[PDB]
Length: 98
Length: 347
Image (cartoon, rainbow over all chains, first blue to last red; front, side):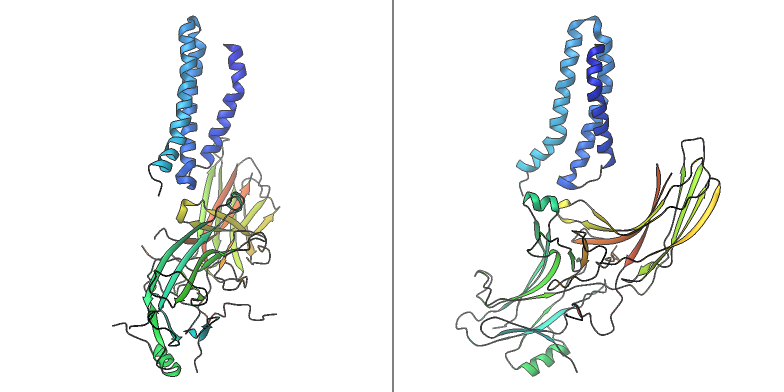
């Protein structure tokens, strides 16, 4: 777990930088406020990572719960990345093509 | 003694006469586009001639141009049947009818308020097409209604400019202040800035009084005073375009727990900003490279239409940073006779 966290600290800093950049430019109206969706995605990704990483470290007692948390974290991160950014874009593309 | 501007078709006898090339607005009312057309009796069944006033709006950015898309829309299109095979006339129109003859068919357009002024974005060397911005055009079609296609020979295209002038009331002078608390205990830094006036004419000097009160543990390195121009693009949700048309950096430092007042002179002009692609400038007819875009006045109690141009003097002090903005209007005054709308010395 310590080695995994050491490997993932680069991605943690990467997410922190992305969230900072998203917060810096939040009110960009391009593509129907795409910056707002990007910022929301970054905020909720930071929230879920902050709520997951200590949980992942502390659930080392049982392998089943550790693996479940590891899978659920990345799965929900993928669903966030899809449904907070591409989903409004897909809805505008398909449901409102005018 | 009065004179008008005449535009003639390449072929046939279709001449459009307009009294003035600038149709200004007074917020409450807009000067009507009044003109006349002479058309020879060369038609048998197509006894209908139409005049269209189009407030076209085009936009293109460097990234968009590279990608291959340029936004285009028609903000307001008005069609008037010039030939009546009601509608009060004016003295100028009556004089034009009397001088031209019986064939002089009048046409009058009442431009609705809350419409953007004629402002054209400055195009780069790569751009060689239609001018980017809001352009007002009058097009005369000698064809059976709008069903038939537009013919270049028949249609008469003339570019008109709708511009606003400085208001009678100068308005309160800008005075912007900002106090910042540093992270090191409670050490306040105070910045204040003021302008000589609120309404500014193009080419006139701008005097900014800046006063700094340092009660901190740091010394200000440099002071950057700039004249930012903002071009809000309501349509297509385009991001705001911000461009520094003039800048001045001062290396003077202010000691902590001390006061320092100074005056700075900034005179925006187009010669230094000629290389800034996408900059908004006054309306153009045949690429005369007019002055900077006059800051539109949103006196209406405020609609998201067209391009909204504004100017703000920004003062920034480093050692994060303290930034303050003072809005001001850079608009032309009312000309005595008329705006020539071209380089008065042609060569």
